[PDB]
Structures are given as C-alpha cells and as structure tokens.
Length: 240
Ligand SMILES: [Ca+2]
Image (cartoon, rainbow, N blue to C red; front, top):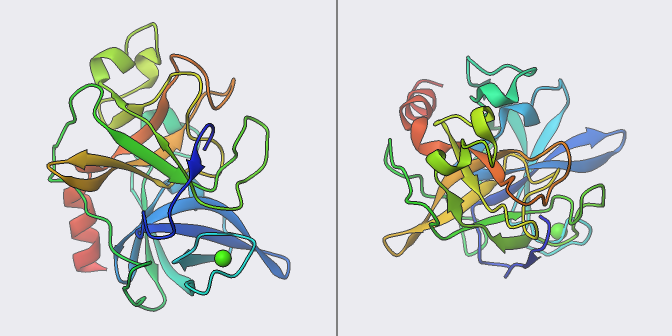
C-alpha cells in the first residue's frame, strides 16, 4: 500500500497473510480475507504457482511475534474455472482456499462480511485498502499492516479513455487514482473494505495496478467485484 498509514491491531480482523515456503522460511506474497472459519478468499493469480502455502490470521507485524497469530496450512485451492493466467484484464481473478483446520475467532480473527449479490457502489463511495504490500513502486513490503482511504470510481468513469478504458470490465471495481494512495505488489488478493449502511463489507479482492507504477494518477487500483461471485462462492463452500 502506497501512501497509507499503519492500522490498529484490531481494525481489520478478517485480513490474512498468504505465505509460501521459501527454503526453510516463509515469505508473504499476498493478502486475503477470512470468510469462514476454514475458508479464505483471495486472488487467483496469487495461487497460480505450485508452491506450498500457509495462512496467517491475527497477524500485524510480519517480522515480529505479536502473540495473536494462528498459523494454518492450506488443504485445497479452488480457482475460478474461467481464470486465465495470461489475461488478468479478462477478469475472474478470485480463488477460495480451504484451510487444513478451522481457526478460533476472537478480537483479532473475525470473518469478513460479503455484500449481497449484484451490489454496485455509487461513485466515490468510502472504502479502505489494507495490506503488507510495497509502500512504494519498486520498494519493499511493509512490516506492519497498512491502510489507505481509497474511494470508488464507477465503471462508467473507470472504463473511459481517460482512465483504464476497455481494460476494465463490469466485473471489477476501481478505487483511488489520486496519484498518492494505492495498492501495490503484495496487496493482491487482499480486501477493499467499503462502508455500506453503517457496516464495512468486503467489496473487492485486489487484482492489479498499472505496469508503469502503483500510485499513478487516473489509474486506480483494480479489484475483482466480489458481489459478482456470491453464487459461485456459496456453491463452492457448500459442495467442497
Ligand atoms: Ca507477527
């Protein structure tokens, strides 16, 4: 997250850290959202490689021990059937991970609330992006969870030539674009929390930013619109 601030230890309890085994150590690679005691929602392109993944909940400082973390393995990975590694602009960047064991809920670990299917936010709706991603284009990961105010930019505006144009589909959500704040590599798969009727709900899964940079004016961070996949998500958690 570029241009953000450190978040409160208990501000975003549904945020998780997806890490892969690097030799004999673990390295953070993406964010995600706990939607069930044993199910995590994240980005498909985050789990395209055949690596060994683990999920960390109750996490705040990636480098230190907060005394609130729970480490659990990933038993099964369910990528959306239409995902295409070579075409992130085609959409469908979403995946579900069944954890090896159910986690215990508390002040630091809670489930994220998903919006009703088909829900579309009005232009300039108040949302926040959170993550341990890069704090600068070509910089380094953050040590502590960061957050940044990132209002939405409706489809009509985001798909106009002055912004992302045709690269953006109606199955996506755009937020930010002020050239100062934005998501960055490492925030992918993480949530976009938006205030709706006095409650924060996860409306997006961080998907991509500009090849030319993370914080680029008129090039808002692009997210997978969660409300477009509610039926899919429910069918997976019920079957698998
Ligand atoms: Ca820690």
